[PDB]
Amino acid sequence: YQVMKRASEVDLSTVKYKAETMKAPHLTGLSFKLFVNLLEAPLIGSLIVDYLKKDNGMTKIFRNTVIPEEPMFRPEFPSQEPEHDVVIVGEDESPIDRLETALKCLPQYDPSRSLHADPVSSFRYWKIRDYAYAYRSKLTTPLQVAKRIISIIEEFGYDKPPTPFLIRFDANEVIKQAEASTRRFEQGNPISVLDGIFVTIKDDIDCLPHPTNGGTTWLHEDRSVEKDSAVVSKLRSCGAILLGKANMHELGMGTTGNNSNYGTTRNPHDPKRYTGGSSSGSAAIVAAGLCSAALGTDGGGAVRIPSALCGITGLKTTYGRTDMTGSLCEGGTVEIIGPLASSLEDAFLVYAAILGSSSADRYNLKPSPPCFPKLLSHNGSNAIGSLRLGKYTKWFNDVSSSDISDKCEDILKLLSNNHGCKVVEIVVPELEEMRAAHVISIGSPTLSSLTPYCEAGKNSKLSYDTRTSFAIFRSFSASDYIAAQCLRRRLMEYHLNIFKDVDVIVTPTTGMTAPVIPPDALKNGETNIQVTTDLMRFVLAANLLGFPAISVPVGYDKEGLPIGLQIMGRPWAEATVLGLAAAVEELAPVTKKPAIFYDILN
């Protein structure tokens, strides 16, 4: 008839692992086209969608189950204990001043990395301090770096279909910015360490003067971009060079990166494989080495998932930690804006500038003052060793590739052997509920904000991948949402209890390596839910509950595809996950040069 539960009293010795994958049909090409028209039919449309809900147990959860927890709409964080051995930074400090305190947290820069590099050494990425050194050593100039990047984009067609890194590129604007930075360096007064650094902005973040289309071909007609966003104006105040708008899965509704609107961005490690959504074009341009770092939203693993498939460092900050004023996901309950970079030193620097909670999030969330980790490890490595690592073994090994579970376990054994971290066995109850509770809490505000435009006939101007999800999102009633917010309160109490025993929850970022692109899906898209969900298996926790997570590269699988490990920490614990990710990077640095890679500063 019906069933019921209660979170604050579950016997955690009997909790069991829900290992049922999302079994939904995958269609490509013309079969996908007629299937979307099936869902958008006035009669047989809702019948097929109601079958998909009932099949994957989403009806039994939202309709045939009693929940005692009260509705928790937004993440509500308790008063957290202060982080150990950090540097408190002002929340209203100018990002110029914040970058300076961040430079003190870094180890002293060795010029042996930039110039006089040993000819017989391994592969390495160029860091932000590498460019900041050659700019001040008059070895090069931001104008010369801009002309070299503009040439690469124009030569290989990275602003044109079918394989573009960007979907809005103004070469005449980049030269205008690089000239001002070059002039400031010649005058001898650079703004900050980020002065002259090339940063790519995702297409769902307002960056002047480009319009914000979010991956669509019509959003600029309805949405006007009149001023910079919060994260962009902070980078521009530091002197950073804003490259252009990055390719992305349309409106964030996809974890593969299929954009049958501007072309699917290809993985720099293998162009025949997917790069990972939703921040698809932003994580690829960093992995290819064209720019230092890139910003992007993350409401369902959009920053961490492609950072693991491409082999870069993606930072998912705490809910409300980084302001979102001026993006397509303002007011959302699972989304933030985190940086994607090639190294931990780079991503940490970008976070130092873009952080700063909004005035609305300041009073509602009450964030602790932002603090940077002392990444100079002397005296240190006593705080790294005292960390308790939470591992759900059954959850840890539920990956479709045995190399991912083995390499991620190697870093756990390496972290326990070099610093002394204790791998504490944990358990995450009600994981299938976290799936259903997330999918509705991310699509409901998106479908709501896009409804006045879809009702305005512009729904036909959307891709088939999005309209397939939008057809299912319309099947979510207001009663379903209220029941789902109660599930968020349950999982919030579970994870808050886990953080009483451990400090971070270490998990593989994705259940699979970089998957091959089905060639039939490059025409109008696909609807593989078994694949688009298997990537979200480990990243939903940080979104539904607002936790900060970070995916740091740890190695490569059999076919040489990168592997990323996720480190999710306590609320407002950016310095804790960044510091541990630095020890992981030191224990497993990037060594394989990707296929599509462009070495700058020759």
Image (cartoon, helix red, strand yellow):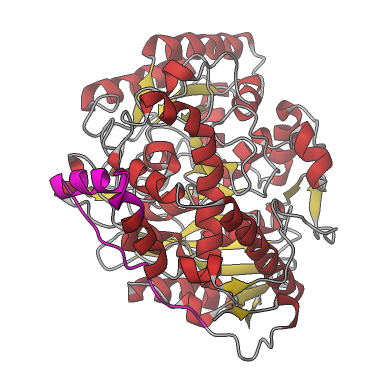
Indicate the quadrant where residue 568 lies: bottom right
Relative placement, left or right, of 521 versus 387 is left
When the figure is inspected, residue 187 is found, relative to residue 276, above or below; the finding is: above
Q: Where's residue 309, x and y in %? A: 37, 54
Query: Could you say which is closer to the camera, residue 24 or residue 482?
Result: 482
> From the image, which quarter does the N terminus lie in?
bottom right
Please report the bounds of the magenta region as a residue range.
17-46
Q: Where's residue 139, x and y in %? A: 47, 22
Query: Could you say which is closer to the camera, residue 321 or residue 473?
Result: 473
Residue drawn at x 31%, y 30% as measured from the top left = 460
Query: Could you say which is closer to the camera, residue 26 or residue 158?
Result: 26
Relative placement, left or right, of 283 versus 77 is left
Identify the residue at the far front of this view. 43
Residue drawn at x 38%, y 37% as measured from the top left = 250
Q: Where's residue 556, x and y in %? A: 35, 63
Residue 91 in view = yes
Relative placement, left or right, of 147 versus 486 is left
When the figure is inspected, residue 45 is found, relative to residue 281, above or below; the finding is: below
Residue 380 within the segment the image draws in magenta: no
When the figure is inspected, residue 267 is found, relative to residue 427, above or below; the finding is: above
Q: Where's residue 459, x and y in %? A: 36, 31
Residue 591 in view = no
